[PDB]
Image 1: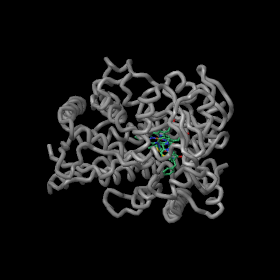
Image 2 (image 1 turned 30 degrees about the vertical axis):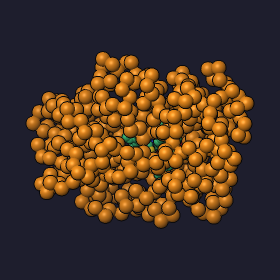
Image 3 (image 1 turned 90 degrees about the horizontal axis):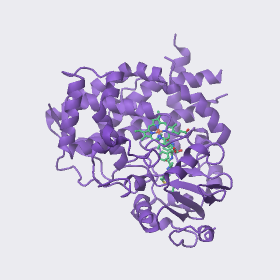
Amino acid sequence: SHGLFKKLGIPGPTPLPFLGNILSYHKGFCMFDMECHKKYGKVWGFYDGQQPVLAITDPDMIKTVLVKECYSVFTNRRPFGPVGFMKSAISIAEDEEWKRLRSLLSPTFTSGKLKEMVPIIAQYGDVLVRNLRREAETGKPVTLKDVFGAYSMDVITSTSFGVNIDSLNNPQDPFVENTKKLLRFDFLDPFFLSITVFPFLIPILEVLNICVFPREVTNFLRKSVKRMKESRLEDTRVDFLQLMIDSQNALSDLELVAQSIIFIFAGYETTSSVLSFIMYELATHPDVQQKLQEEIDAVLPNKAPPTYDTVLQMEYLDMVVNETLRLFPIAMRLERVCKKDVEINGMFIPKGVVVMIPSYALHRDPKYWTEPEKFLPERFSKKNKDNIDPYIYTPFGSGPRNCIGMRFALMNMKLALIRVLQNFSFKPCKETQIPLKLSLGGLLQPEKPVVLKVESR
Ligand SMILES: CC(C)c1nc(CN(C)C(=O)N[C@H](C(=O)N[C@@H](Cc2ccccc2)C[C@H](O)[C@H](Cc2ccccc2)NC(=O)OCc2cncs2)C(C)C)cs1
Ligand code: HEM
């Protein structure tokens, strides 16, 4: 296996027996991707254990695997460990299975359904400002992840299940406590390092009922979803939950739970993380924060409530969101398994190979971005906008397998940002880590929580 890239004429770091190039992930795989792009150029290959991983950076080639040949050859993501029943979760499912889950869940975020959620989200936006104002009162340092996380949990559960768990008023909320423990992918943990280097273990762990997701956490989610499912079949809004309930009358019970777990995690974890990164960038760039507040005041004079339409009018807010996602992409890498031998744009790719798009590296690539390490919202303005390649910058992925919650995530975060900024200003304090350093974990997260001071306007 370790002689594949050598044989095909593809550059790459020399692999070690059994480990492949996995030890290079000691200072984060993003740095590894950066160094490989600089050292080897437009394409290179490395090995995760025995698994060949081909990294591509050419726009047209990226478009070919993410869009053109999605259903035909690059249909699924890389298997990543024992998943138990979560094998049915849409993001983990493959081929035809994934195809039906996709069409089934697709109606969830139509433009019409998104608009209906605005007032629902607003209730939580109001509680968010209230909680933050308390922090502004005491003047104590604020851990963004907690407050923004509770807001995110409340929003995803209400809009998806029509149930208000009121996380914004219950700090030890079991939903957040459990969800934040759902997946702690860490290469320093022997379990995750082992299954990544030796995939043959996966089948064995599945028999043993050993899962990457803690049994205690999934049990909790399973019970929680059942409860909410009941409250709906017993009471006298077509939402995520309804869509799945309707299918049952070919979706099985655990299967419905599997999708629910994906939505809860994405709505809570992924959303609150990006909000934290955005507020960090705003606190360390007062001119950007000041300028953003002015746009909001101009569009919504005297703290007027935001609306679906006015959210879309805010050009700078959108430039700020996009720029933060460029520097801190939750998708540090995008991947597709090559499920059959094929050539694309002049390059041959053997079956079984994992094709990887080093997003984090491409976003900081000194060919497409001047001053790549700088937070400059202007690069996304109408003027410079069209000069950004649609396949170099894909924070939500692209093609048939892209983020199904993209429009909801952008709308929800923007609603939060608006309410918060039309009431407060965030400033860095003593507990604020600057520069901000990312953890080496599998998911996009800073090493120490982002802490900031909130001041009332
Ligand atoms: C060595 C290798 C295995 C590793 N790769 C990475 C980066 N890459 C490329 C990944 O595909 N990492 C994977 C991942 O994020 N997979 C994903 C889609 C994706 C791809 C790239 C960037 C962001 C989202 C999806 C995985 O099926 C998971 C599994 C899961 C279920 C419940 C709670 C947490 C996780 N599904 C979700 O996390 O959906 C949540 C979300 C929805 N939108 C953004 S995240 C895994 C490790 C789970 C980190 S470690
Ligand atoms: C700012 C927040 C978010 C970001 C940055 C984001 C980003 C991504 C990315 C990069 C992928 C991988 C796509 C690919 O491989 O091409 C993904 C997949 C997915 N996301 Fe998100 N996401 C976010 C929020 C959400 C939310 C809130 C939901 C749902 C409510 C959601 C549901 C999904 C699903 C189900 C998938 C898998 C799609 C499939 O396999 O068909 N995401 N997301």
